[PDB]
Image 1 (spheres, each protein chain N blue to C red):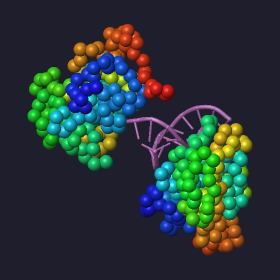
Image 2 (image 1 turned 90 degrees about the horizontal axis):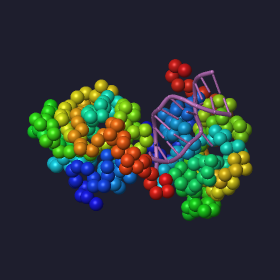
Image 3 (image 1 turned 90 degrees about the vertical axis):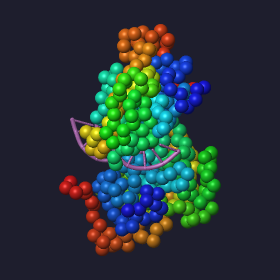
Image 4 (image 1 turned 180 degrees about the vertical axis):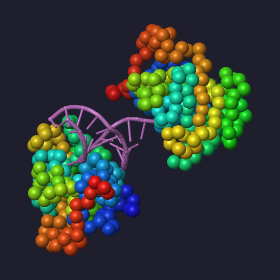
Length: 188
Length: 189
DNA sequence: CTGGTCCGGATG
DNA sequence: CATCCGGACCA
């Protein structure tokens, strides 16, 4: 195993790894919570997050994407929201957010793109949940959701991984080379 | 407003009340699901159900009727909503062969809505819309091969036990009239 | 930022 | 009759 609060890639799980259900992603250690989009500790940082299209105003360019906190009424920079913000190379600011000094100095975040992400993203997988590698918080800030109309906390993530992204020619060749296929639970 | 897990009649909604669409029945609190035939919770009981003639082998005598579980197609199982309705029966739960109530009137109450779509199998269904017919209780339930569909279904016997008279009786008809109960459409429709 | 389930209603 | 367009509810 690895500890629940492990930063960085999970040993033995290559980028391009794909599981049918969230619980499988949880078993593999890649994203512990079965439901929540963010795994983190509010005084340490965030270890991983899931892109599943929950917010219609989010955008995804593959190398970069915006992401939304949780917590309808206004969100606050608390709990998991605070945790992800702490990954950014910048002082914590729960009033106007912050932009990183040197973005690559941020703590790494495992990113999982779900098929449900096709609602807003062209880079999301056709099926299941795909591990897409390590990203870092460039900046975070509060804003009124265009789609929902209450204050949300938004984050800009930028990929910084030695493993090639699954949609690139190189990443596609590697998935094939490692025979990465959609994993169903035993019997299912 | 009553909680979603309320047993018994909805306050202010008399037997004989009729709504054109299922969503209206849902908004009145009488039957929460917009689509499903059974509202319940599988470790509690069932609160309401809708007769809309989806199973051709069901029978209806007004005071009593048989009802069919869902989940079925493959065989049905005594799970989810099926299990919920079974829990209403005054008897130990038995997911192999079912059970019959010791004292049927001690069972948990079930709100029954008869849909006009029920006229496929029943002469007690209304000509139009969805009608609240009052409180029924599960007398017994058992698994059986559907005569009309060929797979195993869970079947239930429901029996009326309500102080409010049934809509099709002389008394119920008088009462619907006296209360000016009419088919209700959504506003504007 | 689950997953399974579902006795509608409209359309044609 | 087949297909779509969905959500609400619960485990």
